[PDB]
Image (cartoon, rainbow, N blue to C red; front, side, top):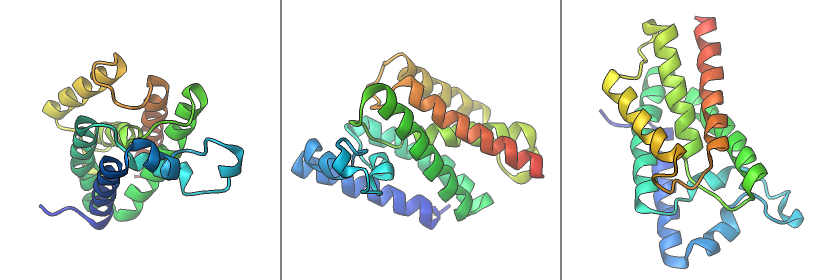
Length: 182
């Protein structure tokens, strides 16, 4: 096993941040890490990304990170640190954007990024079994469970349905596009 530098740094950062929220409280951390919520904040460019790092319960961070380790970890080892970095930044900003759009700047978590990873590992598997990357049958099922729980608000997973589809779309676009090049 052992998980690559992008996979690892991101887990650490989500933990460190979650601790900061436990210590200072949520709003205090949000105040610093959330999508710009006043015009005077629009040029603080980390906030278009760092909403991805804040989680609001033990379950949210636990499941986000399990998925991230398993999928982000697979993507990194098989297909490179750069691929994982690019899926993450695009899916982070686009789901950030749609969330923001429909329901305001108060939100957080890696749930958008995880949906992009699920769609990406799945569609790559189907279109190019040859690259080393597929979502196992069993796991497809547990991905679906995790998705359904989110979609029907069975576990409060910070982001709306509109933002997770944005995440998914990015994973599919990029899988789509990668399976064209091979």
